[PDB]
Structure formats: C-alpha cells, structure tokens
Image (cartoon, rainbow, N blue to C red):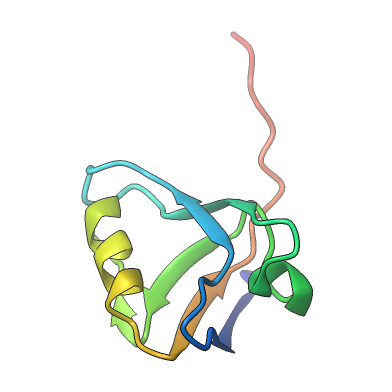
Length: 95
C-alpha cells in the first residue's frame, strides 16, 4: 500500500535543506530531488530523495504547479509541516 506520513520541522530562521523538483503542469508531482549536506532535513533523517510532497503546512499540492510549492515553502514560518508519500517501485520500460 501507499505510505503517507507527515513531518514537522522547525527551521529557526534557517532553511529546511531540501531541494524540490517539478514543473508548472498542475498535476505533476513535487519531488524531493536532493538534500543539503549537513542541512536540517538530512540531519533528521526523516526526509528522503525521491519521495513526493503532497501538502505543505496543510495546504494541498493536488493539481498545484511547482511555483505554488516554492511559494508555500518561503512563506511557511518557523515550523514547516510536510505531508509526504513514499516513492514506489518504478522501473523504466523499454519498447
């Protein structure tokens, strides 16, 4: 089954240490593409590359473009809550 969990991080005026990827297509997923070495996200060990962000501070990203996710993140506040879905067994198909 799909694994969805939520994490609340306190950035204290600092960054989360998370780099996300996506596009402006309303329904493309917002993916954690990399983590800053030594950053908060990495130090918690609770954020992983490849997982997708479903909501930020309770604001759903369903049908929202990357620009909205970036906006939600820089307008978050001292604490940021991320609803995350674990990546699955996706393998490239050749034809």
